[PDB]
Length: 352
Image 1 (cartoon, helix red, strand yellow):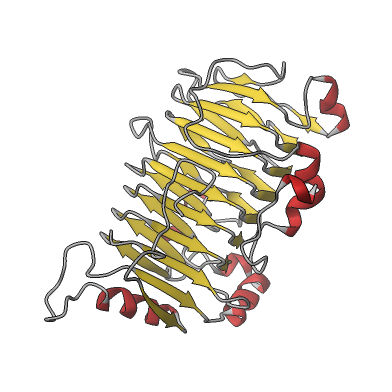
Image 2: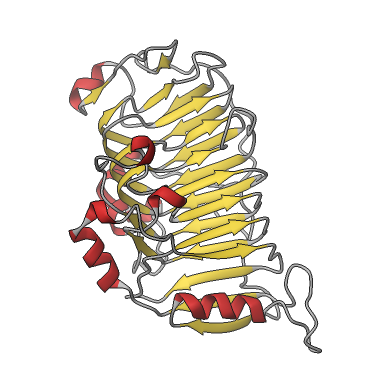
């Protein structure tokens, strides 16, 4: 099946002729991918010779725990990450229950990639692009059921005072269709952008069933295109949530917002404000702000906040087939489906 509940339509490496391999470490993954590029005669095949399903059984809790104890010592270390560059035969990286990684996954110019059940946290190298997950010029990518975390904190003396830790899920370039679902993202200052600059506008991204807790900003920082955010649990947002920019369009439905500052806004450009269609969220009118502790702030440049909590534009017909649960149900149940070790469980109406 290729249904991801969002714009990405992929089965990753779970296709016909897929070869399954077990990675017990970061290096194993690197080696497995390199080998997957060679045909029967040892010659290299552009985009990969065969589809892969890599089960990662490694555990790096020691690194994570050491890092959690010395937060400000991470940014200056060398970044660590597996690069999945120009691999298009289809690939899935599934963490085994109990596995953990203190390294990221950087997807570049690939297609049909699925990253699931990975517990990634406290990555070193925030000053040198130490992203947890990066999707660059890569369409049909599905980031599902992962736990991405660090500390929602900025240490003193870091370059640009923004490099204590890098992003959880950055999407940029021609990553035309992407689905980010069932992830448990917590303790992350910059969750993820959708377009690296003002000129990097476009893409159709879906964020569904994610549980955000204690995050500062970018859920996402959207530049153009379309974003469909449904059934997400947004709690303890310390800066801003969905920042719809460069004329992007967003459909924000059936989500639960709580203890959030500027949950839906269009700021920092001073122009080309994006639009949003609000529906089915726990907040239905400004009266609810007080109830769910939703505060708003201004910006030094022209900006637009959804403080009137009204739709400011339109949204095209949602191409795919999805069945959202109610905002209340996500609030009640979501924490038990999002993240690692939930056996890729999905929240259905029957569970409400």
